[PDB]
Length: 473
Length: 48
Image: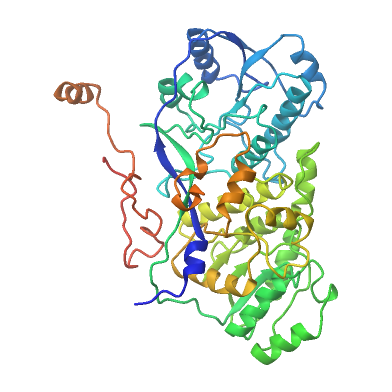
């Protein structure tokens, strides 16, 4: 018939787990670290001991507890010698701090281990095991997104220093056979692969897949109250203008200060002329009591229909000397706010649900290690909602052409290799198309593939960017 | 081989894992909260 949509058609990308083969079994010697922690002693200890002694690896038992700084563990690691393997078992069969889900002991502990190893002048890959952190298909169910945050931060660390990371395997919870049948085929596999997910038959790896744009005719009802967090906040104001040009008598453009932050005259004039009196905000979002107040502020008729969590709590993502508590306090608003909205809208009927994440979480660019845990948590929450039957979306977005706060020297660095920019006008129709075809976690970013390859490959071999022929340049 | 089939019968297991991924199926829009939506399946597994 016609397309005329080549830009958005080439703008779409996915993440999928193609089946993978095996590497090379090894019969080698070396002091293998196990990081047994304090309460992690389980059948995994016996399995690892037996397997490593069969492979000849010297299982180096170690006991670790809550954050111990980043020096003493390095000092005790200097007293054993060269460690040829580390099996991070810290995240298995562990609950989560529901009060502060972003603040987990596992991420801080493993970051301290990474820093100590860096100070330990060893340079051994740190292999980590997860339990249902990722799904190779919607038929599976994910029970935690903090493990996804660990995945993202580990990928960021891998992109930071090649010699320290390597190994992010996934094992189903309460399983023995998946580890038993592969073992050295993955932990000592010669073939370069890191996003391993052991499951039943074989293994899988995260891979980039360009999506398609089948024709559709549905469209979400433009009217109805819509919650848009972050207030004006640049991108948020542009989305508000887009909604006004679509037509909505009432919405909710929540900011931390709402009208007291900016207020503006042009924004309210547009919202009134194109639409009608649209409530802005009365309080913040990071507090559950604030969510209760916002719920109490809801009137009658034209009820809530969509939620666009465009949080503006992003400050920085540079690793340097990170701490888990620092990441938690830097990303309080988006995680706690998203959790509050999820729990407060369990029974309420909604038309759309957009977490509105960002890019640099699929690959984890350097200097953006703080946004990745939040993006992973949003993606996990969206997956939980979709598997539970409730609508959700986990769009990941790049840098806007008119983004005043989200475009600077780092945007110039991305411009000099890879993405140049993207006009926000096309973002509206891209979002409409994504919402049309029941999408969950779509990727909308344009990439100059040759520059991206020459800036990304460098010294780390990776098969993640291999399944797309347009990236052969 | 038939011998492997007999072994499986003897140990008494099942071969239900999930939908494949090599055939290039969409695998995403195959399900929805509404079961009456066109192009939606119901089975989340099976032996393939």
